[PDB]
Image: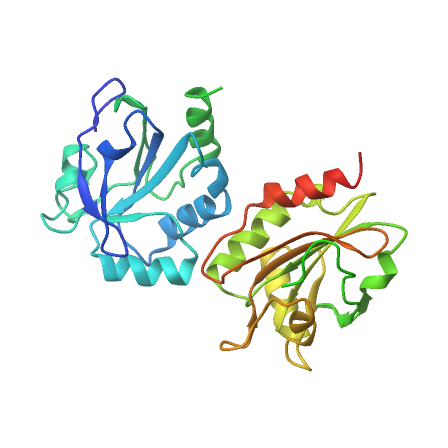
Length: 153
Length: 153
């Protein structure tokens, strides 16, 4: 897993509507919270993304953007997003399979899915926060807002 | 949609506990926040109401009261409220179907559901804040608290 201080691998991925989303596009404009998750329609990250949806104003505003990423293709993310109320971007690290996840050091080579890793990328494209919690343990979202809050005022 | 300056159409609707709630009952006592919503058990509605829930003291206090309104019947709002931890009123604009929603000009004729209409009704019963977003769009709740604050101090 890339650690704090590393330049964040740039990427171009399709969101749930088949639109292209590039990390570079936020450079100089917004800090970016990257939430990698293993698989759509599973218990743990459903709860995790539900928290994100419920606190969206803290993640998607004038100073911050939030991007969820997993290896699933757009149709999968669209169905789940629509059913779950995910109005933020769910990006497909689908083909190449897990290419971005591997570059961030959060890919499970054995199962073929991304681990629950989280990073905050600043306006310079530098990783300023990196998190990877133990299995079965949900991530601390108050932590993400604190991290984001430190990169503003 | 009804706009600021209009008298808010009065109503008497059943809440999730089958108790009668009438809008006029708040006149001369509290400003009322009306949050219409398309349907219970849907994603974006869940997110909006979880946000309201998470910040309830800001909408339900000495100066203000909040009522969420939808076409669903009492049983439907009761289960959703209990599972979601919603302690505020959820009113049934059920039969006649969406009559109140139609009166406020926020009823979606093709789908048979209220759109995301929000209103602030002051102590005289006049609409002081109005907005209507689509079922696929998300509302900015800061606008809600801001308008409620303007009728207080």
